[PDB]
Amino acid sequence: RLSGYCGSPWRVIGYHVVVWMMAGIPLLLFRWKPLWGVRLRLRPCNLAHAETLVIEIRDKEDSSWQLFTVQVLRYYLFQGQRYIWIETQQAFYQVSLLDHGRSCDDVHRSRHGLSLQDQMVRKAIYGPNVISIPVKSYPQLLVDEALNPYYGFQAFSIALWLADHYYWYALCIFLISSISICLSLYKTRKQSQTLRDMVKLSMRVCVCRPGGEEEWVDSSELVPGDCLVLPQEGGLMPCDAALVAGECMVKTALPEGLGPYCAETHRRHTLFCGTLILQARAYVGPHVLAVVTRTGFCTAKGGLVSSILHPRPFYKHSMKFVAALSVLALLGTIYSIFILYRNRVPLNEIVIRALDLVTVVVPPALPAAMTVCTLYAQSRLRRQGIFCIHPLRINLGGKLQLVCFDKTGTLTEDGLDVMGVVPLKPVGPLLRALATCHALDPMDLKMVESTGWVLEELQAMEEPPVPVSVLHRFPFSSALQRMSVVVAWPGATQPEAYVKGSPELVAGLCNPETVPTDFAQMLQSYTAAGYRVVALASKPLRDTVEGDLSLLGLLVMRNLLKPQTTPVIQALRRTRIRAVMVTGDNLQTAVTVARGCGMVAPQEHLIIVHATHPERGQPASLESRHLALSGPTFGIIVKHFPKLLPKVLVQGTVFARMAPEQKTELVCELQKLQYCVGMCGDGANDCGALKAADVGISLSQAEASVVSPFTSSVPMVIREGRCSLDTSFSVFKYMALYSLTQFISVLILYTINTNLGDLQFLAIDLVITTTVAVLMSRTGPALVLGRVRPPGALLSVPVLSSLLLQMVLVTGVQLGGYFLTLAQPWFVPLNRTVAAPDNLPNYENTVVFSLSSFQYLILAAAVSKGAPFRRPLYTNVPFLVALALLSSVLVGLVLVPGLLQGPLALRNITDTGFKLLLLGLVTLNFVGAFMLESVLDQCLPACLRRLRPKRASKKRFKQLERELAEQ
């Protein structure tokens, strides 16, 4: 929005590096909120005219960044946007230093290429044509990424782990983390490699020089004020240019001249990059003449890359949870120190054990949290899915309330047939027009095949009865969907032209030629039920061809009924999710389907604005009260913003008759209200929609093709869509639960003199890793389409209450077990001077270890979700077998001592509490916990806060509540 620029240069050199090195450690914590850092010695507060370093200060825009200034008059880079500094106005200007306004074209016509101006300044200006395309080596990127807080924590954790006499134990997991970082490096390198797909290859083109000399130079160099040359060999035009002479067929010249440039109706002369050239007409020689407009980086080709690179997108809850853990550790450190001092151990080598315990208090359940969702991508590959190269935003897209659909080139499926004769009442002109209506979409091919015509993939057969031969054709673009073709009719009798397009588009140009009286009501009655119509016109001879045209009739066709999407829509409707579609075929072809599918029970009406004049109103036109949004309607009422634009999109049902150019704007507007709206389309008219959409769906996109952010391989969409989000939420809950449990157990089980089996620490790592906790990452199709929607937030009243009860119960049972030693033989252990590493498991260490392990197993068995949330635990045979084996081996330790007692050297246990008391207490605890979980997870949140769930900042619920006042 708005901000300020300030800075200052260095005063001298010789001790700045020394100061930085000495004060390096505090600077690590200053990475966040650099505002405090600008007040240090780094800013001597010199004059603003000479700074050599641009620092952005937040005034109206948040999310401050860091900028760098370099000297090749001064310039600096900011998010890929080049800025030029001038000493005449004391300000920074964009790439258009003097091209901000629309100057006259007389100067552009009178130019004669380069002049005697110094090339040094012409290079100091914004410079050559290149793109960001950053490349880094493996060691460089490795060292750069080593400073991230996430990676730094792992290094500290492993370093402190090594101090606790664990070399073969922690080294393996450290190597696993390192190879995971290597996989992340590959992840971030593959995207960089893909970025290099849009860059063209270097080629030599002619460059004009003043007076009478011409030279050839590579495209790597170019400066403003030169006549560019585009040879036929060149496929990609190096930079944006506007034709000045000749003609092009991607454009015409301007030999007549014009006054002030408007760039509104004279767009036929400007040519943009990123589009191939088919044919060009050259007046002089085989080359062309043009200008050099906005060029190089920051252009369209580079502009799209910059827009998708720098500003590309709920971590506040995670940060708050991390801070909570940190404060808990800080407040428990004093207690741990007091307990250690209670044992009278003032040795220096042992006090650091308290700090080691503080460091290890936090479990490693933070680097390893996405292992579960990786296997889901494998399952999608196994059966089906739209997995991308690097799927990492499943949780982000877990929330959604609107699902889009496409019909222009997605529905219906392939297949079409003719119905009957035209309603004009076989006809010469009709057959002649139809014969040339081909793109050799497959729809035209099917039509020509059905009508009985054979044509070359220009030449055509059956000449004697109907001589037809194609001569020239125009390309089909996204906006203004139409196809005009010029054929070689002059042979028969005279030149003729034909064009096919939507009736609405052609209705705007046939007014002065001929307007049939029965064109509106008849068309409405005919197309009111499914049928789609296109308008055909002829001209007996891109603006030149659209001068005069005559309509030849209508066209009735039917694609298919596709009796497979309706069940999908009905199932989606049962989840309180509204379904919408976007297309540009016809409003009457989209309203008809809306009345025979599960999104609205009653008949929905539509509203049409009067015209583009400033006297627009809001009339009431007929076909629970949801309105239908038409193209021109919003295209015209895009004006005054405080007219409650956000408050009408929700009430709308269909957004159609909308040119694909505004797909990105529509997606941004929908997403601006914290509403994640997906996309479901194909073709070249949904590139921007998918690029600017967090989640996208495609059907016609196959493998080995990178066009959409999500690449596919209509009915198998919702089944794999909602299930994926539900499973992601379930696994995230499965982690956070039992992660809090691991934290509290590690913090609590340290009973002053219990080492928890230092040599047996692997007994838990090989109970959690690969067997049997991280397992059960299976697909979770409940086979039901109910209204189940678990929360996607780590904090929530039901989960929090369940966790509080869980810690209360575990603390109580642990205290009871600890106090149970009173009614048992004392058996006082050895005296002090060991305090831990003596490894003296006699009657408490192994007992507590086994009890804790069994408690983890019981919680995992009971905490599992039910049938409606996930599949039953008895359906996955491997997981059930693993759980049974683990339970059997655990029970065998306390069942009877055999040969296993040799290596581990388990001590004897009194028969009084060997088979009765422990079994009774553990089974009672298990049944109590199961009953508590069943009671709590049944209907707690509903009966608690169904009506007023403390509405504070819930935006979606805010709109939901506001909708009531609009009824």
Image (tube, rainbow, N blue to C red):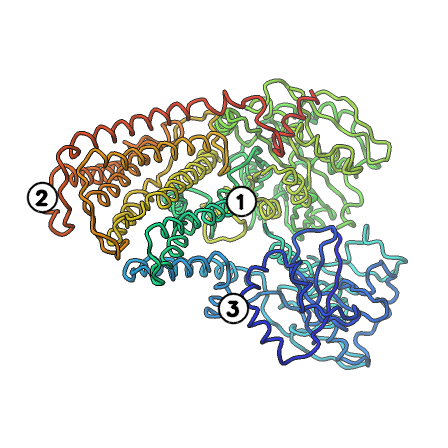
The spot of residue 198 in percent (x, y) is: 58, 61
The nearer-to-camera label among 1 and 3 is 1
Mark identifier at residue 360: none
Relative to 403, is 289 above or below?
below
Q: Which residue is mark 3?
A: 136
Which residue ends up furthest to the top in the rendered image? Answer: 602
The spot of residue 363 in percent (x, y) is: 39, 49
The answer to whether residue 838 shows anywhere in this view is yes
Q: Which residue shows up at 81% across the image and 54% down it?
A: 263
Q: Which residue shows up at 32% across the image and 42% down it?
A: 773
The spot of residue 450 in percent (x, y) is: 54, 36
Q: Which residue is mark 2?
A: 898
Tell me which amino acid carries mark 1.
Lys
Foreground residue among 80 and 908:
908
Q: Who comes first in sequence, dot 1 or dot 3?
A: 3
Relative to 793, is 290 above or below?
below
Q: Which residue is mark 1?
A: 320
Instruction: State the image quarter where residue 49 is shown.
Output: bottom right
Q: Who comes first in sequence, dot 2 or dot 1?
A: 1
The spot of residue 75 in percent (x, y) is: 73, 70
